[PDB]
Amino acid sequence: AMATGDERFYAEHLMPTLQGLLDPESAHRLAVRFTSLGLLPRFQDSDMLEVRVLGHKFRNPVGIAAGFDKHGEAVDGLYKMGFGFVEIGSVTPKPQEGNPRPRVFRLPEDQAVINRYGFNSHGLSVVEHRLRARQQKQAKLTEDGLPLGVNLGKNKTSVDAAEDYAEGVRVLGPLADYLVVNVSGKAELRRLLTKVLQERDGLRRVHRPAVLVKIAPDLTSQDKEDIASVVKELGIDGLIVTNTTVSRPAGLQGALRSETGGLSGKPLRDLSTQTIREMYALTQGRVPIIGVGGVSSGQDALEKIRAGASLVQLYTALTFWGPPVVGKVKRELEALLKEQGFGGVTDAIGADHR
Ligand SMILES: CCn1c(CO)nn(-c2cc3c(C(C)C)cn(-c4c(F)cccc4Cl)c(=O)c3cc2F)c1=O
Ligand SMILES: Cc1cc2nc3c(=O)[nH]c(=O)nc-3n(C[C@H](O)[C@H](O)[C@H](O)COP(=O)(O)O)c2cc1C
Ligand SMILES: O=C(O)c1cc(=O)[nH]c(=O)[nH]1
């Protein structure tokens, strides 16, 4: 009824109007500004959405994926939007501009975006001071089941990938509930992740974040088997499955389908779910998975949960549906959980594998 009306209006009228008036990067920039200022209305989270994972309570399992709030400017407005957790970044050590504009492209016919931002970042030091300003506010949020993740990048020109990520661990690890490293042979991955975990383990017990590895959906079977093996061997805390795809699934209609970059949204959905499914099996259900890629409904959310995800993220659906999508996904997920006989989200995790 009321929520649905709001959802209708945003999906059918407001967002298409606003996206038609703006270039896509301007739209992103304006969203971050509006969100930072809390210019949003406000769905009471039931107990059945609560998840305990990664050393933390999550009030609900629907997170904002990396890339929306690259520089940690809008964290409080994102909780206000109703996300159960927030992931900022990617943040690189040094400030960098990222790629030339235009670098974001809408494929509205496909409910997809292509981006090639190229890790535009304010840098660790700006983001550190920004999180420091609200550090105690975040400690209370985390305690109340609303944790904060930080995705760490590397500078375009850097010689030593591992040292960039290490810098990130040292600077932002003390302010994060979890840290994320994106990965694109096996001995080099082990070397990199060893160094990351060593740095993490050197932070004082109360400032010690979980470390997650975030994979694209474009990896070979050999890459996925090697990642599962290294993740288990090293005691990596979790996996974020997946980033955008450099593939172009047959059937894209948008005029901008041949733009270089990462494809997100609906055409990534089932690629992403199947990657969750394979990573869950290769890790024997022992490594918590955050599912991401084309979530715009409770059904999308539940398919990833049942495939092996403990938590989900979305970004692209926000570009088409606006802020009401968060309440929509949560409400539909709750209803689906009851319809399939699950007492809560926890019971559904990996339910397809059993
Ligand atoms: C991929 C880059 N990218 C694109 C282009 O593909 N769009 N986009 C978003 C834009 C918006 C906008 C724009 C249209 C002004 C407003 N609002 C919003 C709000 F922030 C506060 C109260 C009302 C509204 Cl509608 C959103 O939530 C929102 C979210 C997005 F992800 C975004 O990150
Ligand atoms: C504009 C844009 C910027 C992104 N930036 C980042 C980033 O800096 N780091 C990262 O790990 N993922 C980034 N992502 C990937 C998302 O976090 C997510 O994995 C992907 O978009 C799939 O989810 P979706 O289909 O819900 O958007 C970005 C995605 C988009 C669309
Ligand atoms: O900044 C970007 O280009 C970017 C980073 C990332 O991890 N994923 C993505 O789709 N874009």
Image: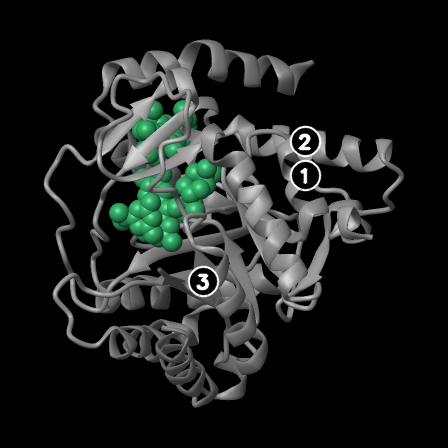
Between tags 2 and 3, which lies in front? Answer: 3
In-front residue for pair 270/4: 270
**Circle 3/circle 1 CB separation < 8 Å:** no
Amino acid at the residue labelled 3 = Asp
Q: Secondary structure at mark 1?
A: helix
Residue ID for mark 3: 223
Residue 58 in the image, given as x and y percentages of width and height: 65, 56
Task: Check mark 3 vs ligand 3: CB closer than 8 Å? yes or no.
Answer: no
Q: Secondary structure at mark 2?
A: helix
Residue ID for mark 1: 303
Between tags 3 and 1, which lies in front? Answer: 3
Residue 100 in the image, given as x and y percentages of width and height: 10, 41
Residue 251 in the image, given as x and y percentages of width and height: 42, 20
| Residue at point 63%, 16% (across, down) | 4
Amino acid at the residue labelled 1 = Glu
In-front residue for pair 235/168: 235
| Badge 3 or badge 1: first in the primary sequence | 3
Residue 258 in the image, given as x and y percentages of width and height: 24, 28
Vertical relation: 163 (above or below) 21 = below
**Circle 2/circle 3 CB separation < 8 Å:** no
Q: Is residue 69 visible?
A: no
| Residue at point 52%, 40% (across, down) | 271
Vertical relation: 267 (above or below) 232 = above
Q: Secondary structure at mark 3?
A: helix
Between the C-alphas of marks 3 and 1, the distance is 24 Å
- The quarter of the picture where residue 112 lies is top left
- The quarter of the picture where residue 341 lies is top right
**Circle 2/circle 1 CB separation < 8 Å:** yes
Amino acid at the residue labelled 2 = Gln
Residue ID for mark 2: 299
The answer to whether residue 160 is left or right of residue 295 is: left
